[PDB]
Every structure is written in C-alpha cells, then in structure tokens.
Image (spheres, rainbow, N blue to C red):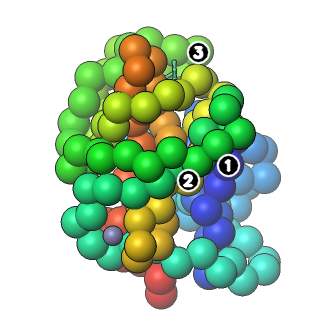
Amino acid sequence: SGAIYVGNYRVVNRHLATHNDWANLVWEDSSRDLLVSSTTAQGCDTIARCDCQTGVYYCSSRRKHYPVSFSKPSLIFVEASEYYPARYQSHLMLAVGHSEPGDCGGILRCQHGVVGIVSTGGNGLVGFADVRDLLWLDE
Ligand SMILES: COc1ccccc1CC(=O)N1C[C@H](C(N)=O)[C@@H](C(F)(F)F)C1
Ligand SMILES: [Zn+2]
C-alpha cells in the first residue's frame, strides 16, 4: 500500500484505489496502473521533474529503504492478475531489488522529489510506475 499527496491530488496504484478514490476520480490509466483522485486537504509532496536513473525506494516487505539504479520509463510486458490480463504496462521503470505484491505503493524518490510508486515485481526485480511526466499534478 501507499499514496502520493501533492496539492489537491492523491496518486495511488489503480488496482488498489478505494470507492472514495473512484467517486472523486480526476484521471486513471489502466495501462500505467495509476489513478489520481481529488482531496480536500493540500498535499505537500514534491514531484521530481528530471531524468534521474538512481534513487531510493521504500520496501514494506523488509521495512527498509533501498538505493537502486532504474531504467527509463517504457512499455514492459506484465503477467495476468485478479486486476489485469497479460499486457504491456506503459511508463514503467525496472530496477534490481526486492518486491512482493503488498509492496505496491512504496515511493521511489531521487534528490529532486517523488519519481514513482512500486507497481510490479518478482524474480529479484522491482517495477515503478513513473509520475514525472504528469506536469498537471503541480497546477
Ligand atoms: C510488486 O509486485 C510483485 C512483486 C513480486 C511478485 C509479484 C508481484 C505482482 C506484480 O508484479 N504485479 C504487477 C501487476 C500490474 N501492475 O499489472 C500488479 C497488480 F496485479 F495489478 F496488482 C501486481
Ligand atoms: Zn531526479
């Protein structure tokens, strides 16, 4: 689990969005596993606007943060689930690191701010849904 709070927005994994998220929907993209809902309180997270390929993510299954090198956002094949059929997930960045399904929502950050959130894993890999291209999150 996990979310990003920036201005009047809440960013979460689309497969983990609640009834409240869907009733206050701003934007969602099934191909990215992202959903953004509106909030009444003002969020104070800073979104990174950069091309960093190094950062730190929080891994709930180990209660630890890990430094990682990660790939540029791209279309990557992802297996079937109770939420999606086998498809290409877009805007995804992979890194070598530990992840388990419950780790989705863990934040990846670089020196500039929030880069993305855990969305995929397995086989000693961890995949992050990028949010740096969502410029409207700041306005
Ligand atoms: C953190 O994910 C791990 C980690 C280890 C092992 C397995 C997983 C699960 C994984 O790869 N998923 C990809 C998928 C997707 N984003 O299309 C996610 C979900 F199904 F929508 F919830 C879950
Ligand atoms: Zn950066």
Decide which of tag 3 and tag 2 comes sooner along the chain. Answer: 3
Secondary structure found at label 1:
loop
Which quadrant would the N terminus be assigned to in this image? Answer: top right
On whether ligand 2 comes within 8 Å of the CB at mark 2, the answer is no
Q: Amino acid at mark 2?
A: Ile
The residue closer to the viewer here, 112 or 90, is 112
Decide which of tag 1 and tag 2 comes sooner along the chain. Answer: 1
Q: Residues within 10 Å of mark 1 (few under 14, many from 20)?
A: some
Q: Which residue is mark 2?
A: 107
Q: Quadrant of residue 36?
A: bottom right
Decide which of tag 3 and tag 1 comes sooner along the chain. Answer: 1
The residue closer to the viewer here, 18 or 6, is 6
**Residue 30, x across and y down, in percent:** 44, 38
Nearer the camera: disc 1 or disc 2 = 2
Nearer the camera: disc 3 or disc 2 = 2
Secondary structure found at label 2:
strand
Residue drawn at x 51%, y 45% as measured from the top left: 66
Nearer the camera: disc 3 or disc 1 = 1
Quick check: 84 above or below 138?
Answer: above
Q: Which residue is mark 3?
A: 82
Secondary structure found at label 3:
loop
**Residue 23, x across and y down, in percent:** 73, 54
Q: CA distance from mark 1 to mark 2?
A: 7 Å
Contact? badges 1 and 2 (CB < 8 Å): yes
Quick check: 137 above or below 121?
Answer: below
Residue drawn at x 32%, y 56% as measured from the top left: 54
Residue drawn at x 65%, y 81% as measured from the top left: 44
Q: Which residue is mark 1?
A: 2
On whether ligand 1 comes within 8 Å of the CB at mark 3, the answer is yes
* Residue 8 can be seen in this image: no
On whether ligand 1 comes within 8 Å of the CB at mark 1, the answer is no
